Image (tube, coloured by chain):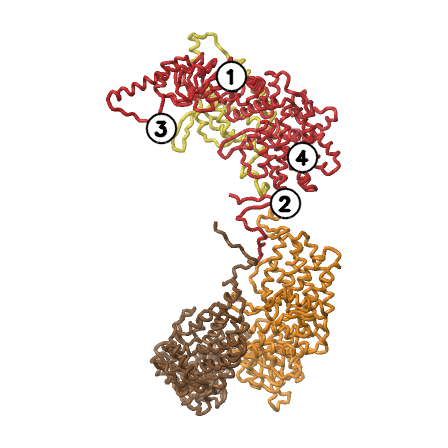
Chain colours: A brown, B yellow, C orange, D red
């Protein structure tokens, strides 16, 4: 009874699947990208909500920062990966605005679907997107409002970094702004290259965020293994050799022929070890730092000559310490070091949060390294605050590289949509359809700000255009209160990051074009 | 390995031919004869035959022994059917006809394996058979004392 | 079947059946690669098992990275693979010709003829096609401007039409600035390096060379000017004796003396290096950079650092060939006769770190005869796309430098050649006339697929081109923008003789061998 | 690893097989036919051997007659069936010579293979076989040497039928010839149609064949149920009605309204039954034969009127008796039958082979039906002898249908092979090769007789030709002794089945042609 359809022409696969055609390949790639854009939409903006994400290692991450959420979502779709990977170049270049990619590039892909069904294929929609993108790069340099040139001090930096904090840590926009300004300014590179790697974070469980502070120096979580824990002169000698003597590299074997050679053998080891420690005691050594273990006799002599020992197993901790205190690490046993020692002002141990730590404090030579000490009741709080610290450190670098600030709060995005649309209306051809849609990709961004803020997006957008009658260009979204009641963004101080907006538009456009140029999908069998 | 065509003539039969088929047929006849070998003569023994239900019959007559053997060999059955005929024609020729027939095959067994076309075997069997039964008629004795006490004593 | 009697699990094809099996597979492959011919072709997404995405349409990768299991397709893949060793591009064309030589033949073999007949005609048709190919060679004196047209013709087919303006210059200049005086160009003198810096259209051409490793000591200079380059393969790490005997001593004091003694062979080798910096008139910066290809212990690195000498380690075998040439130095395997004469020269040496990966740049050489192309693609798949375009482009212009002539463009020869075969069709004086007809029509698969991929009507495009040629003398072909016949020399599309030679020979050998198989079988398992 | 070959063109079956071509279809059909011919070859000829066949019912059948072996062997190959069917038509036509069909048809197909592998296709081999066959039927009328015209009595028929008996029952060729001669003459149809169904066989277990005899009448294996088993006048009435009175055809019910009707009902029925039996007793009848049941009251009255009863449950057995005794079977209850009564000479019962039998013996009016009574020590022997009796009955009919005889013992076949070959030698064309092969098909027949006789066939066949140098035409094969030393067949008395040879060649040829005309075979899925 029941018939079956035969094969057709080329059933030579072993279980692979194939997709081709506008609806089966192109649209499915677009729709898969939309699903990711929706996933991160909830967390978008300072009024967004947190996710609780458990990754494939059963580790729990609680945050709203898409840069770390996307790294834990095990996306397998062969095309959706591309719009996710684009976000890495955004984070690497400027360190902020990663949300732009999924919103803007996602919108360009969705909006293309609205055209590909009724008219021209991707060979023309892409051209319109690329033309309009080039025009956006002519509009944006003319929307710059301020420059971070004047009053380069603690108070202007606290204000300039506000946007990088209040966008994720809503309630901490003041407290964290003060801490991050102290760390960025303390290593001010005399108007040179800002080194983001000279700011560390130390997480110590305890009370709430108000107990966080900045410490001009390094903090380690090791013990002393000795009784010289209070050092005031703090001449620091760092070594890479273990503090237990030295042996040969070929083989080593001790041969004894008679009794006098046996009985007097051990005495030679004590005489050598005493002189080796004395060599640096006579030079004023206060602290000896090693990566290796300490011998029982090494402790005997360390206490004899009142020298504090610190063991740092991490090679990077040893390298950073040498660069902090101004010391050279010696690979050999302790010589009478004369000039290779560093200097601190106060070196001590303290029990903080029921953890004993080693502090190398610099009061005079402050601008060498900064540590930001974060307190909190949960690990989740401290991990999320650290991300806010990194955004501030990166934002400072971006301002150093390019000091121009562009109005935020959706004001620039509406203005880009307005001018780009007007350009499209004057194009004597069919490309105007994608140029106008390129403009709408920008309108999608303040719409996301409206939805998560609890105000009706259609009313917000209508007002934002009504207040931009060719001469304003500055009113954006007020999302701190009920009722849109749109006002000037620059009086409030919402502006930043020219470079990020320039790069983000170029990168996000290219990601959308990359997906649209895919004609056929050839799947492999999973393993 | 050899008779392995794509399509068989019949279905799945067994087939044997020639000298090994006769040797097996004679051997099977020697085995079935064993049932009555010890039942001959006034000093013979009786047999106890049990069926699958546990029901036993005790006897020494071939008319009972040979019918309960449940022989399935195509050729050995012959040495039972001849007892059925003797039971009708003689009435007690039972055990003796099975043993004699088996011996007829044994005596020629060493010769039938080396040529000896079956036609001459049949010719010799028939020649000797006709001679033997003719001699019996020439040596059997009768009486002329019918309807007398002498005939009743003959029956005893 | 005899093989089934011997082995019940043996397979065999019948004489009327094996041909269909061979042709069907060829048609399946044709249905794949026909969609990538020319700049108007499609791009395929190849999804692998690790999750890697390759967005490519190269004929060679599509044939390799495909889940097609067929005994005939495995044979076409072999002759196709060879394309990329001797001519580079042209793989799509190779398969397209083979598919039509096998497909068209079926329309005459099935009509009562023996397969030998069509194959004898195919061999005869090849001879005529080869004679025509010789008559269309154009000598353009291999000017740089001709090479630009060659580079653009090839590059357009592997880029997104924006990158061509960047690679065209990088391909033409990189291939020329290698060797002079009509000496064969060795492509191993051109490097391709990958970085993830900016965008596809920021690929740079570096006059000097870049190493994938940097300084291994914090006191070494990050910027070195007026540098002397020493390229040695010596071993400056700690080594032991061959005989595993070790040391025999009594006292702890001797233990320390043994440490000083066993390392003396290291100081004897390193102290011979520090003399060189002092012999190159060290009254200024006069930087000293030593490559030291093999491993080196931190003892030796620190000994050299104290003297202000920059030293690298763990270089590749091919780094010591290109770098020694580029810097003008002498490759040393020992320290027996060290002198400044062994040192090279570089105006500037510097490092740059991207993503915590160090790249060392040795630049400002006089005539290094070796260049590095630096790809700055934003994504992994973009690094693959460009790298393939670079190495293909370099081959395309190399062939135009080695071959003193160029061949007219994509369809300019294929249509006229097909007409040359038909005009001589009756000259075979026998039954091979059908082989000429099948061959001449198979030659048209290139302008025919190009007409379709560009979106033009198949039949109208070819009728117009064939008429324009027949009534004129110009080698006109397919225009991918208008569909009208145009002359290859005016639109700027060229090919290489080596490509047309292989297409006429390799497709005939394979097609005629396939058509003469009539008993496909499987045995031995 | 290793790929597999795909489908080719017609893979639309559900597991069916298919064959086509000279090697896959034609030769395979011939090969199956060879195995058939070889299976029956061992039993061929008067010196053939017996088969023991166990059929699908687990019954043992032992014989050498291929006509009864083939119907028991479940031949399945579609090619072998074609020859088997022809052998059944030979049995239907003349009843003897069936071996011929498998031997000759097999030889035609084997020899056809020799031609197909070197030369002409079946399109000419078949035509050549027909050309030679047509000539064979012109040779046969010229080989007639005797006729069954003289001495048409019991003595001549005892010699004419021996050739049909010795071919299966070698050692009984004299004893059985005497018995069948007494039967064939007993139903002489006054020079009309010889009705082969008027000779029956009765098998009774007992002593050997020498005790068999012919009884002029019928023997049944039923009882009398009375003490009047010996009847001398044998005035016989036959009925089909049951012997218990009249019954209804629908239902019937007895209505009683008074005691007198109840009391007298049963007694009235007994009085009616008395009259029903008396009706025929008054006619002098001795025996009443029925196929139905007998009531207790019928036996009561049968003893009153001294009536012998016989019950014959088989309708065909009773109809045969009606024609034997000269009576009509009446479907109605027993009237005083006067003009439809039968008569025998002696009707009695006896115990023969421990079976109680009823004998209806005729001595004066003998030629109505004859029963040949066979004895034997085994059922297997008696079944085989019965088949030998059938051959004698059917052979007599064949001799009546065509009274001409040609020499046997291979003499006819050698003359056909020689004369047919001479014709082919004069044909100026390629048909001479198939004509000569048709002749060789006959040579295979006396070769089979030699092989089973223990004599070297290559020398025997050389002698059979050597003695036919244009002036003999009568010497055949002597299979009675080692070293045949061939002798005249007419002096030997070996000659029979002229008509059988005529039709056997036609049926054997048609079977061979039918096989050869099959070039392509389409099979159904096996089940």
Give the Cα separation between the discs numbered 2 and 4. Answer: 23 Å
Give the Cα separation between the discs numbered 2 and 3. Answer: 67 Å
Give the Cα separation between the discs numbered 4 and 3. Answer: 65 Å
Residue at image mark 1: D216
Residue A517 appears in the picture as rendered:
yes
Residue at image mark 2: D21
Q: Position of residue C89 (x, y in %)?
A: 64, 69
Q: Earlier in the sequence, mark 1 or mark 4?
A: 4
Q: Circle 3 — which element?
A: loop
Whether labels 1 and 2 belong to a single chain: the reply is yes
Q: Earlier in the sequence, mark 2 or mark 3?
A: 2
Chain for numbered disc 2? D
Q: Residue furthest bottom?
A: A151
Whether labels 1 and 4 belong to a single chain: the reply is yes
Q: Are marks 4 and 3 in contact (CB under 8 Å)?
A: no
Q: Are marks 1 and 2 in contact (CB under 8 Å)?
A: no
Q: Earlier in the sequence, mark 2 or mark 4?
A: 2
Give the Cα separation between the discs numbered 1 and 3. Answer: 44 Å
Q: Of A325 and D292, which appears nearest the observer?
A: D292
Q: Earlier in the sequence, mark 1 or mark 3?
A: 1
Q: Are marks 1 and 4 in contact (CB under 8 Å)?
A: no
Whether labels 1 and 3 belong to a single chain: the reply is yes
Residue D307: mark in rendering = none
Residue at image mark 4: D130
Image quadrant assignment for residue C514: bottom right
């Amino acid at each position: 009874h029941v018939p079956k359809a035969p094969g057709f022409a080329q059933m030579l696969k072993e279980g692979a699947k194939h997709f081709s055609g506008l609806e089966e390949a192109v649209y499915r790639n677009i729709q898969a990208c939309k699903e990711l854009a929706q996933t991160t939409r909830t967390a978008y903006g300072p009024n967004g909500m947190n996710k609780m994400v458990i990754n494939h290692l059963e580790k729990l991450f609680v945050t709203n920062d898409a840069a770390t959420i996307l790294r834990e979502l095990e996306v397998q779709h062969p095309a959706a990966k591309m719009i996710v990977m684009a976000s890495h170049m955004q984070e690497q270049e400027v360190g902020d605005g990663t949300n732009f990619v999924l919103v803007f590039a996602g919108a360009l892909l969705e909006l293309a679907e609205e055209l590909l069904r009724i008219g021209l294929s991707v060979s023309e929609v892409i051209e319109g997107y690329e033309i309009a993108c080039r025009k956006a790069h002519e509009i944006l340099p003319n929307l710059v409002c301020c420059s971070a040139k004047n009053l380069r001090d603690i108070d202007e930096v606290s204000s300039l970094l506000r946007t990088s904090i209040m966008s994720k840590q809503y309630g901490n926009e003041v407290f964290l702004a003060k801490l991050i300004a102290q760390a960025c300014v303390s290593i001010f590179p005399d108007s040179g290259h800002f080194n983001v790697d000279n700011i560390r974070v130390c997480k110590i469980l305890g009370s709430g965020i108000s107990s966080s502070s900045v410490l001009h120096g390094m903090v380690f979580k090791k013990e002393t293994e000795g009784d010289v824990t209070s050092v005031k002169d703090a001449k620091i000698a760092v070594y890479s050799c273990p503090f237990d003597g030295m042996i040969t590299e070929t083989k080593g074997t001790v041969l004894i022929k008679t009794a006098e050679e046996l009985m007097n053998f051990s005495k030679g080891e004590e005489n050598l070890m005493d002189a080796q420690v004395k060599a640096i005691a006579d030079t004023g050594a206060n602290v000896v730092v090693t990566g290796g273990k300490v011998a029982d006799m090494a402790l005997h002599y360390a206490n004899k000559y009142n020298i504090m020992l610190v063991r740092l197993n991490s090679k990077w901790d040893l390298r950073r310490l040498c660069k902090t205190v101004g010391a050279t690490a010696l690979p050999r046993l302790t010589p009478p070091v004369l000039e290779e020692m560093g200097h601190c002002d106060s070196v001590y141990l303290s029990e903080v949060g029921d953890t004993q730590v080693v502090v190398f404090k610099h009061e005079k030579e402050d601008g060498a390294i900064s540590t930001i000490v974060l307190r909190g009741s949960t690990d989740n709080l401290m991990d999320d605050i650290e991300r806010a610290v990194d955004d501030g450190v990166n934002t400072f670098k971006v301002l150093t590289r390019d000091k121009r600030l562009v109005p935020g709060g959706g004001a620039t995005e509406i203005e880009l949509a307005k001018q780009i649309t007007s350009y499209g209306e004057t194009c004597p051809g069919l490309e105007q359809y994608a140029i106008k849609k390129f403009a709408e990709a920008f309108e999608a961004i303040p719409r996301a700000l409206a939805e998560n803020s609890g105000v009706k997006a259609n009313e917000v957008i209508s007002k934002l255009y009504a207040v931009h009658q060719e001469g304003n260009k500055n009113v954006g979204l007020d999302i701190e209160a009920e009722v849109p009641a749109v006002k000037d963004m620059l009086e409030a101080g919402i502006l930043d990051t020219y470079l990020g907006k320039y790069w983000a538009i170029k990168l996000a456009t290219n990601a959308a074009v990359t997906v649209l140029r895919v004609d056929q999908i050839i799947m492999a069998k999973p393993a | 390995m050899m008779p392995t065509p794509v399509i068989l003539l019949k279905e799945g039969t067994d087939s044997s031919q020639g000298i090994p088929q006769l040797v097996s047929n004679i051997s099977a006849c020697q085995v079935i004869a064993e049932a009555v070998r010890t039942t001959l003569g006034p000093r013979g023994m009786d047999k106890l035959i049990v069926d699958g239900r546990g029901k036993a019959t005790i006897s020494n007559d071939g008319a009972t022994i040979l019918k309960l053997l449940d022989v399935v060999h195509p050729a050995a059955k012959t040495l039972v059917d001849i007892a059925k005929s003797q039971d009708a024609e003689v009435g007690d020729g039972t055990t003796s006809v099975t043993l004699l027939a088996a011996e007829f095959l044994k005596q020629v067994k060493p010769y039938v394996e080396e040529g000896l076309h079956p036609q001459i075997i049949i010719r010799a069997f028939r020649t000797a058979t006709q001679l033997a039964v003719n001699k019996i008629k020439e040596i059997a004795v009768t009486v002329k004392k019918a309807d007398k006490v002498e005939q009743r004593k003959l029956l005893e | 079947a005899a093989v089934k009697t011997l082995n019940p699990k043996a397979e065999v094809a019948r004489a009327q059946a094996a041909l269909a099996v061979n042709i069907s597979a060829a048609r399946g492959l044709q249905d794949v690669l026909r969609t990538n011919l020319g700049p108007k072709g499609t791009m395929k997404m190849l999804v692998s098992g690790a999750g890697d995405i390759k967005l490519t349409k190269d004929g060679n990768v599509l044939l390799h990275e495909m889940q097609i299991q067929h005994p005939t397709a495995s044979l076409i893949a072999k002759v196709a693979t060879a394309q990329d060793d001797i001519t580079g591009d042209g793989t799509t064309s190779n398969v397209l010709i083979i598919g039509e030589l096998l497909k068209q033949a079926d329309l005459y073999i099935s009509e009562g003829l023996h397969p030998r007949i069509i194959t004898e005609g195919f061999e005869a048709a090849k001879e005529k096609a080869l004679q025509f190919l010789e008559e269309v060679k154009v000598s353009r004196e291999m000017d740089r401007e001709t090479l630009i047209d060659v580079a653009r013709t090839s590059l357009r087919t592997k880029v997104h039409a924006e990158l061509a303006d960047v690679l065209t210059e990088a391909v033409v200049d990189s291939i020329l600035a290698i060797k002079k005086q009509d000496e064969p160009i060795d492509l191993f003198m051109i490097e391709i390096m990958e970085m993830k810096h900016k965008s596809e259209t920021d690929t740079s051409l570096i006059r000097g060379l870049v190493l994938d490793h940097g300084a291994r000591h914090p006191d070494m200079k990050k910027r070195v000017e007026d540098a002397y380059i020493l390229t040695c393969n010596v071993s400056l790490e700690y080594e032991k004796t061959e005989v595993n005997s070790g040391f025999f001593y009594k006292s702890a004091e001797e233990r320390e003396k043994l440490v000083k003694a066993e390392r003396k062979f290291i100081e004897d080798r390193v102290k011979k290096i520090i003399e060189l910096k002092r012999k190159v008139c060290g009254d200024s910066d006069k930087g000293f950079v030593v490559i030291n290809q093999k491993g080196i212990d931190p003892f030796s690195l620190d000994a050299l650092s104290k003297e202000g000498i920059v030293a690298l380690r763990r270089a590749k075998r091919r780094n010591m060939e290109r770098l020694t040439l580029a810097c003008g130095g002498v490759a040393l395997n020992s320290f027996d006769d060290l002198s400044p004469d062994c040192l090279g020269h570089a105006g500037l040496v510097y490092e740059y770190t991207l993503g915590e990966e160090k790249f060392t740049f040795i630049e400002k050489c006089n005539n290094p005869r070796s260049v590095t192309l630096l790809i700055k693609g934003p994504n992994k798949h973009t690094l693959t796309q460009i790298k393939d375009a670079v190495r293909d482009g370099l081959r395309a212009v190399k062939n135009a430098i080695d071959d003193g002539c160029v061949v007219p463009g994509a369809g300019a020869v294929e249509v006229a050649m097909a007409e040359a075969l038909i005009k001589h069709k009756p000259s075979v004086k026998g039954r091979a006339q059908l082989g000429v007809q099948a061959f001449a029509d198979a030659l048209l698969i290139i302008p025919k697929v190009l007409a379709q991929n560009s979106g033009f009507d198949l039949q109208e495009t070819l009728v117009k081109i064939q008429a324009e040629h027949s009534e004129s003398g110009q080698l006109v072909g397919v225009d991918l923008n208008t569909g009208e016949p145009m002359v290859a020399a005016e639109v700027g599309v060229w090919d290489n003789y080596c490509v047309k030679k292989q297409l006429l020979h390799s497709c005939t050998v394979i097609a005629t061998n396939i058509l003469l198989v009539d008993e496909i079988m499987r045995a031995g398992m």
